[PDB]
Length: 53
Length: 71
Picture 1: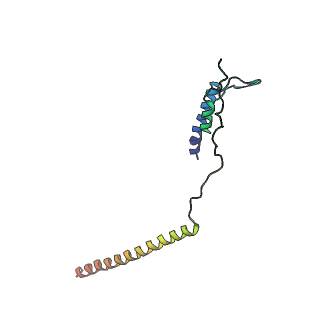
Picture 2: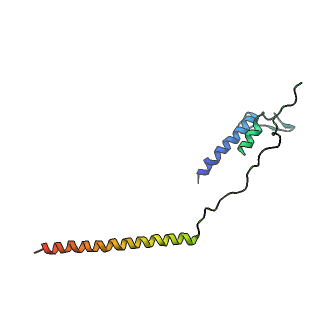
Picture 3: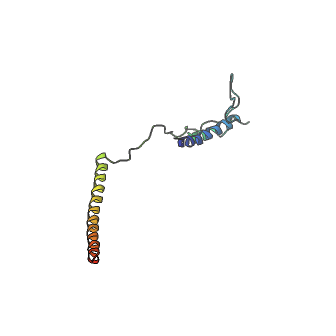
């Protein structure tokens, strides 16, 4: 098919932007730790997640 | 002095988020599609009938001209 690959990898890039904003890394974030999470969400992250979803 | 300030949802929450599958049905019955196909076929048949009869008459005219010229 090969067309939906691009169509949905655009959305995958947006979710990678979410990953990078929350941890500074696009894929291997290492955000979830055995005590919780490393850092709190930036002040404008929830609004952008709502806009994407 | 300053109060707690961190990433929180706005008061009243967020707006609704659509998630249900939405594949609309555009709309034309199978009977209608078959009827349209048959109608265009019949119209083409009639047009070609008229044109082919005219072509037969034109060919007869050309043959008559040739026959007149032959001797």
